[PDB]
Image (tube, coloured by chain):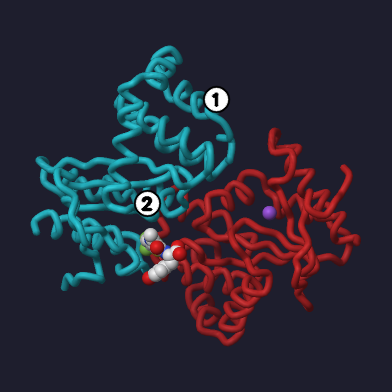
Chain colours: A cyan, B red
Amino acid sequence: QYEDGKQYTTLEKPVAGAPQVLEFFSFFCPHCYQFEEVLHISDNVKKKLPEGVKMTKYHVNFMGGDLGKDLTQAWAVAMALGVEDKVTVPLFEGVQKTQTIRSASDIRDVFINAGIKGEEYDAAWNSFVVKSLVAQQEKAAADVQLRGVPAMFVNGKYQLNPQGMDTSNMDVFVQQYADTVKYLSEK
Amino acid sequence: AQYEDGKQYTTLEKPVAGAPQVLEFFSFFCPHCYQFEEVLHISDNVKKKLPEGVKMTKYHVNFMGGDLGKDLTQAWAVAMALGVEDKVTVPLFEGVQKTQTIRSASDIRDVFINAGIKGEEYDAAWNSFVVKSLVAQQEKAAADVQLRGVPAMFVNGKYQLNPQGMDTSNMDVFVQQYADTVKYLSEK
Ligand SMILES: Cc1nc(-c2ccc(C(F)(F)F)cc2)sc1C(=O)N[C@@H](Cc1ccc(O)cc1)C(=O)O
Ligand code: NA
């Protein structure tokens, strides 16, 4: 029983050439921590979607002050090096659980400890490839008039509405969320 | 340590009458709350340094958890009603955050049963007026201190701990600084 306003909302001005599935998060975002560590939303959405569908995940600037911008640049590094899955957990825990991530250096340490060579990290950090990925993340958020995280957009036309879903059972919530993404992608 | 308003603690503009002597707020969904309790043992270390007669109170809140969050607050009310907080705190934190075995109210109940509380006793407590009242008490206390987030601790409804705020460069030092601050405030 899908209804606009319930499981999802519809953007007023759809974004052209938008990614099929686009997620925004912040490492400072508490629901984003839950979505990644506890619920594994991205993994479960991926499992429910066809192989052909591309999922994109971008970091945002508007949580966490100066460190917030640094983390967006760090996420650009992770995308450029293809090590998202190596650093997502220690970045989330470093920010929200242990609160040991306080500076860019602390972010660098996380990449080092996750097996990324220091020289490779620094080269990426300062690269124009990464500068462009930072620009891409910012523009994407601006295109959908992003006001908060977590957020997921389907074909630049629909936005998921987790608030409209059932939150008594974690796996029911995940099922309803993932099923909504599939429904919207086939729309 | 040299204590100053605004440093190790802040002072509520609207103090709360009849508040518990030492009141801690947490959520089982809250990862820094997991850090506080399961890793740092803040509650326990504060209690060790508390003066004789001063009891600790700990309430559950629901900023992140939706309906399941409400179930957790009611289950925490049951833990308080039964006096089994020290038996279920660990498996609730680990079950929600680490093993991800706690996904519904039924899984919460299973934790109490595995910790030695009979199912019929858990259910009796769950549906009791005592637990209904305790749920309301936890909410009201959070409202009274204008709670913004967790973890948080309040002393005599007048002072709010400010860990920000403290030497969080060494976890052992942080814990003693935090516990010493609670002792100081309780003595004022
Ligand atoms: C993004 C988000 N995700 C949530 C969620 C997801 C899963 C689960 C479960 F445990 F079941 F897995 C619980 C909550 S609330 C939530 C969220 O946006 N929460 C709001 C408050 C709110 C909560 C429930 C409503 O029906 C309406 C408003 C806030 O934090 O201010
Ligand atoms: Na605190």
Q: Residue at x 47, y 21 (%)?
A: A112
- Whether labels 2 and 1 belong to a single chain: the reply is yes
Q: How packed is label 2: few (under 14 Cα within 10 Å), some, or many (20 or more)?
A: some
Q: Is A96 placed above or below A80 here? A: below
Q: Is residue B82 visible?
A: no
Q: Is B175 placed above or below A135 here? A: below
Quarter of the image with the C terminus of chain B in it: bottom right
Which chain does the residue under circle 2 lie in? A
Is residue A71 rendered to the left or right of residue B90? left
Q: Position of residue B167 (x, y in %)?
A: 74, 38
Residue nearest the viewer, comparing B184 with B159: B159
Label annotation for residue A105: 1
Residue that carries the numbered disc 2 in the rendered image: A35
Quadrant of the displayed image that contains ligand 2: bottom right
Q: Quadrant of residue A159?
A: bottom left
Is residue A140 rendered to the left or right of residue B65? left
